Length: 291
Ligand SMILES: O=c1ccn([C@@H]2O[C@H](COP(=O)(O)OP(=O)(O)O)[C@@H](O)[C@H]2O)c(=O)[nH]1
Ligand SMILES: OC[C@H]1O[C@@H](O)[C@H](O)[C@@H](O)[C@H]1O
Ligand SMILES: [Mn+2]
Image 1: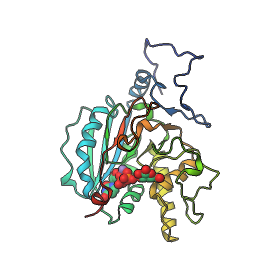
Image 2: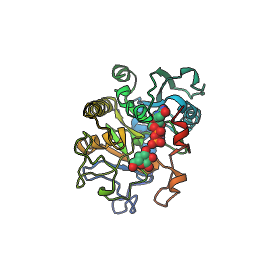
Image 3: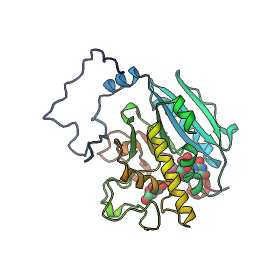
Image 4: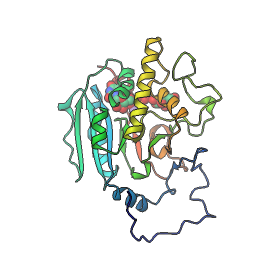
């Protein structure tokens, strides 16, 4: 049951005046695409605080990637769901390497020890298995957000993202035609998507939803990866290829714009991005991914 909102004074939405004319703000299946200017965060914060929403955030920090936790967590404290209840779940092979980060009230951090796989592909792919923990999350949080660790928050990331199931536009592909997307193109893979299909190219580094929908998605991607492995095939972009196939066949109920996953070193600051909210931390793939 949802109680009434209180009285609020804010600018009237004007029907004959779009919030944004330069971008698509709704998908053809009627899911909002979340850009700055499309939401009044005061209304959304009221709606979500009246439900006492708890948001879980999963992040894997395996092997050398424990070096990224301190900045990840400290900037998450400044920008991620401030005001709301947050439960961080840090999955790591080195619990003693997790930094002691000071948290705001109503926020908590659990360390979950897991095994480390040797190949960075397997570390990244096996997040889906590891996330799909199911009983714990159902009891502790309302939504789950699943992100890469090699990142920092630079601006607000809040309840405007929450919905039963979301993906995020990949920042290198948001202006690309579908034939250029780097979907898995071999029909022998469970992740396969033909050249005339596909809505968007979603990035593996930021997806989420209600616990039930996120467990559905990670269970389906893990089972699809297992099928591929048994068939001796590994999709071209690993978990990201599987996430893409899942979100093609199960349309997300919101899509985040590239505000929410950006790489300023590689892509700069285009005018279409009014805010850069969650951004890549520069790293040397070869070095950090190997002993
Ligand atoms: O040795 C590794 C390799 C990957 N990851 C996790 O897998 C995610 C995806 O890998 P990565 O960020 O290397 O992919 P990229 O963004 O560079 O394509 C990382 O953010 C970490 O959460 C990890 O913890 N240790
Ligand atoms: O083409 C897909 C790839 O695009 C890259 O820019 C990104 O670093 C990879 O992780 C993968 O998403
Ligand atoms: Mn990453």
